[PDB]
Image (cartoon, chains in turn blue, yellow):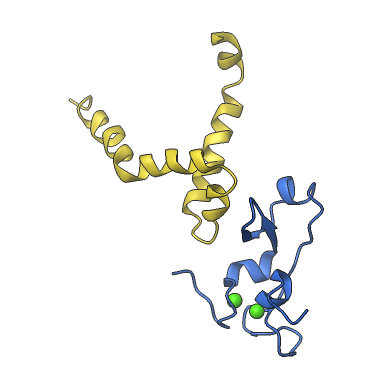
Length: 72
Length: 63
Ligand SMILES: [Ca+2]
Ligand SMILES: [Ca+2]
């Protein structure tokens, strides 16, 4: 089990140092930022707070925002 | 060919030692599985007994 302080789905080392969300076949996948792969595909590099369930204190987690599991 | 291999095994060495770091930095091993699912299994074959036969086959030459 990787550590997770804020229980927001994504691990602590990914929030501090960068991450992104990619799809491979038709399956979402939350992966750390690799500039060799993810930059050509036009993705974004997210950073958040490893101790806040929602970094901007709204009622939507950092997992729900970047993935799409949100009110549309 | 044994010449291109002999002249470019440095990049054949960086290609392995990079994937060794992905398999054991525990936050991102799954970035190896969904971007290279055969290199992941090859390192899984190493970790599940493959490292034993490369460890036991050196002390037998330690005589
Ligand atoms: Ca977290
Ligand atoms: Ca967070």
